[PDB]
Amino acid sequence: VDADTEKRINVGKTHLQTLRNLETRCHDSLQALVVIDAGSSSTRTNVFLAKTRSCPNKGRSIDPDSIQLIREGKRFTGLRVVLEEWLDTYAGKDWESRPVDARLLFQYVPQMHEGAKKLMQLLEEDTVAILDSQLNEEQKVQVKALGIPVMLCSTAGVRDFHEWYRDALFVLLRHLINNPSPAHGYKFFTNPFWTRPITGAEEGLFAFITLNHLSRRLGEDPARSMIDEYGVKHSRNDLAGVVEVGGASAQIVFPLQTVLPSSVRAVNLQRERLLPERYPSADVVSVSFMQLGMASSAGLFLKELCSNDEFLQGGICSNPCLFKGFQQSCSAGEVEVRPDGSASVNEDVRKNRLKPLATYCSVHNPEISFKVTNEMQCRENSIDPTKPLAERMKIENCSIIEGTGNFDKCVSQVESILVAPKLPLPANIEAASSGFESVDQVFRFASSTAPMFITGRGMLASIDTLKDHRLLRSDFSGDVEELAEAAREFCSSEVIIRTDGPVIQLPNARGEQKLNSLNFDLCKTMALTVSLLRHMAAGENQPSFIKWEKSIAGPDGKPLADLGWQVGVILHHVLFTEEWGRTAYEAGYSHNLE
Amino acid sequence: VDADTEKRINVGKTHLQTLRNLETRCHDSLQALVVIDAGSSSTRTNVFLAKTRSCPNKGRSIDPDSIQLIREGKRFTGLRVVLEEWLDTYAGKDWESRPVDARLLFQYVPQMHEGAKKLMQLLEEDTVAILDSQLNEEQKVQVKALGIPVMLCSTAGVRDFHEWYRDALFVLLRHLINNPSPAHGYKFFTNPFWTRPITGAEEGLFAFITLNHLSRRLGEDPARSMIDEYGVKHSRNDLAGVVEVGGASAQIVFPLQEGTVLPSSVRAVNLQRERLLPERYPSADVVSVSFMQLGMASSAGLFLKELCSNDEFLQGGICSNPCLFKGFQQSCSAGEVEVRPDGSASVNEDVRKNRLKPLATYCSVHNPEISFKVTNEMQCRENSIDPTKPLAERMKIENCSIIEGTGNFDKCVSQVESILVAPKLPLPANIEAASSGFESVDQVFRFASSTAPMFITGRGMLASIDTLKDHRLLRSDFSGDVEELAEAAREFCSSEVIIRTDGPVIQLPNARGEQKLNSLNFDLCKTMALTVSLLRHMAAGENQPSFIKWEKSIAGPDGKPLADLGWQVGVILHHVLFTEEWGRTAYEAGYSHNLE
Ligand SMILES: Nc1ncnc2c1ncn2[C@@H]1O[C@H](COP(=O)(O)NP(=O)(O)O)[C@@H](O)[C@H]1O
Ligand SMILES: [Mg+2]
Ligand SMILES: [Mg+2]
């Protein structure tokens, strides 16, 4: 038995060594992270999962490569609607057309809290439902014990919001997040660093961090970086830049490979505390343009084009960005392409694409009344700030809009109205302060050889549409003339109303597609793309390559998260190990214990 | 025109980029580091060079791999002699044999400072001479601007010093180091963390850090370590242990392997927990034990005393020494030995030169460590030293006139085992070893053992193997084979001393050849016997070393050794590796902490 009992001695000795190992090693645990996207059109939850690691005498940290989106939630009320509804009730209806004493609105702070509460309860219910459905029991125990950091950030929707209203709303939003329902057991918590409005530049920087993280271009490890003989860490692969065109604004972000004019303000990632010191350094141009988003540029373009006598004659506005055979009521109201081929224009003021701009452009807004600069920017886009809201949004002496399907005239107008206007488009003090009045100035003062990624649903639909009809090659790499010739052909299509409804009939029997509420004005976006590509092509430095991407595939061939600012905002916080440990784990949800 | 000016534009753009580069990059600078070895036989300087790097917003640090010894200086007086000389003058002569009121010695602190000053001025002169001779003008500018950290550490020589004397001396030594001659421009400086006595365990730990650093076994980068799936950093190669036999003590150091079973009485050191290495370095549990009286000089004195007080060896005034060659004869004393050109051995009569002085000085009834502790008195009496007798009779080998060599290796091993390796009671001044759970060398491998490879170091330890290799008695690839070593040494140690015209010679028994008889090899057979005994004890351990190597030096990246084996590199590393603390003490406070 001295070989049998000997194996028993080694079992007992192993039991002690295993136990000793368990008390010396690092332990992994699952954490949930929540990003609330408070956008122009809606407020939506984004539920993420990440792997945390705790080591004896080293604390706890997140493995940044483990960050994965589990679900993007339902589209609830935007913050603009919350504030505008509260103003309708407490400042009275048509406060957009009258002087409002903002001081008097302070007596209605509890009522603003009640409005904000309604939205917060829906978002909490949505977040909890996603968590309950995706996690198993063991995962829920970990997720519930660690605490759930919440980052609610607002973008272009309330970026141009007047007076003190928005910032008071943020104080209320944080209080609501810090008091979740005790019933579900999920410990949601926030602070003024996680929950706040983000600037257009930050928004762009965060989307740049997301892109480079997911594509594996950004990293501090030997796989993604290299330390030279002088101790400087360089990224192994070029960091790529990003163009993101959303609903309300467009972000242009690129790392510099440089010597800049004194007027241009570039961001150093380390110096500006976006990335920790251990990460490769980069000087990045990040500029955001209000009125360049899909919805906001649609409203502005109609208003400016249909007020020019070259386009407006005897009640008819001739729109070169719209198809031949397409007709709509002369308004910036939301368009619904109906099954019968008709274009239904929504007359509800809240649904009009000019509402945000016409609301900003008011003589009762201190930004207009005290600043001639801002008034002239408004008047340059045919908005008279002295007139009531209804006439500010109205396209005067215009009954009907008719499409002419003339792509070059469309490009020409997109260039003069949106890309290279005489004055900066309104609510762009931030872009102007960084040295850029308009899109045309971006590539004139700063250019880079850094590759570029073009993002945004509409930007992608523009290329994918031309690819589907075999008008563009599947390997399209940004060729301007190739894009202009493809779009010139597609945009000269006739709109035919058939039994099966409105159809885009391509010239040269090249086929067809259905006309709908998302693609009826896609030609304006193709014109924006062409104009943008020409401006990038004119820069002293030209991108090494240009790519259009819907998503970035993870290590298993499947994307781990979406493109956008959400992953970036998480990384911006979690990468600063010490600060994150103190705020997420030391203080944590227990900071709220009352 | 446009092609040529575009290039001219590119020269201007380059001029700016070169300067942007300079103000963004890390910059390298040379620093000198000084380790003063305050050992048992002497106090000697060790001048090192290291590359420092300063990075914007990261401060300054030393590249540990750049540490190189430029020179080990002259052997000046040991701290023991400084203190005993001071006692001779202020407590009076023969204070070793009389009661001394230690309280009264406080009035002589300035005089202790004056004695210490004499030694410090010699060491400073030696250090400055080494620096002036090795550095060029650009190197001197860097070395002079950065400041020169000094680490004076005392070992076995003053480890057992009585009363408060030694610690008062350290306060004076630091003050002297912090006030260098302004003339030479080298800005030497120290503090109580760098300049202090070091325990035998620390001494062993530092020699272990040196060995593993130089051999590239110890490291924190992907080349020398690996991080597992659970975030634990392991060394890529096995960390090796060390046996170091110096002049006064011997250190035994080894890392403990996975699932090691330790009795509660055995105290192993965790490198990170005990702050020897920073957290970023692989963790290890290390047995480090030091034995006083196991050094070359101290064991020579003790061995003679014990062997020649034994009736099996002492008869008719002749002590028969089996550790000494046939035909070798000396005066019966532990006094320093000189092999003269005529073949005669002259034993030095000077009490300060007698190898028993440190032990006989410790073993006194007027030392509170003996008078209050029967334990210590019994340890002394077990080595034939009566602490009640004057110094002269404590050092004397009674009724013994002549020591004659018998060249009997097995009798030599037998005696080294009973006297030195496995004595009845622990050898005196070993409370530190005893406190860590080890009374003697024989207990080290009984209580703890490891599969960790072992390196055998020390001047005598290497001479023992190299001598047998030279006479082709041992193979060049000797890996520690006990019977092979005993067989080789038995043959070599049975050699006869022949007195020739060109001086005395060691004649090998079977025309195997010969070598010159000198003051360094006359008693080498005791060290061979110590080696054999040590190897048998390691071979008896539950876990045996993967391999045993005898090394004089460790080769650097260019085939040439960067530094010596020993505690010196280790003590530097122990401080420089803690980046933040080193930056604060060496650079933020620096030599300017001393500014008037
Ligand atoms: N298939 C499609 N074709 C063209 N445009 C499309 C599309 N799907 C969405 N879009 C456009 O993206 C925008 C969606 O807005 P978001 O990306 O949510 N930006 P924000 O609300 O956070 O500010 C809409 O304005 C819509 O016009
Ligand atoms: Mg958005
Ligand atoms: Mg020594």
Image (cartoon, coloured by chain):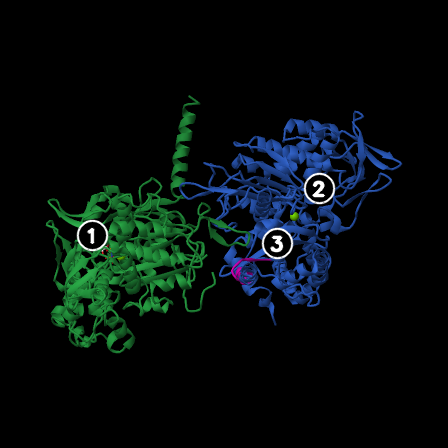
Chain colours: A green, B blue
Q: Give the range drawn in magenta.
A: B14-28
Q: Is residue B125 left or right of residue B346?
A: left
Provide residue A208's location: percent of width, then percent of height.
36, 55
Q: How crowded is mark 3: few (under 14 residues within 10 Å), some or many (20 or more)?
A: some
Q: Is residue B409 left or right of residue B274?
A: right
Q: Is mark 1 on a helix, strand or loop?
A: loop
The type of residue carrying mark 2 is Ala
Q: Name the residue under label 3.
A: B50
Q: Which of B583 and A428 is in front in this view?
A: A428
Provide residue A46's location: percent of width, then percent of height.
25, 52
Q: Name the residue under label 1.
A: A518
- Chain ID, mark 2: B
- Chain ID, mark 3: B
The type of residue carrying mark 3 is Ala
Indicate yes or no whether the magenta region holds residue B25: yes
Q: Mark 2 points at which residue?
A: B300
Using the rendered view, name the quadrant where residue B337 is placed: top right
- CB contact under 8 Å: marks 2 and 3: no
Residue A528 lies, with reference to residue B323, above or below; the image says below
Ligand 1 within 8 Å of disc 1? The answer is yes
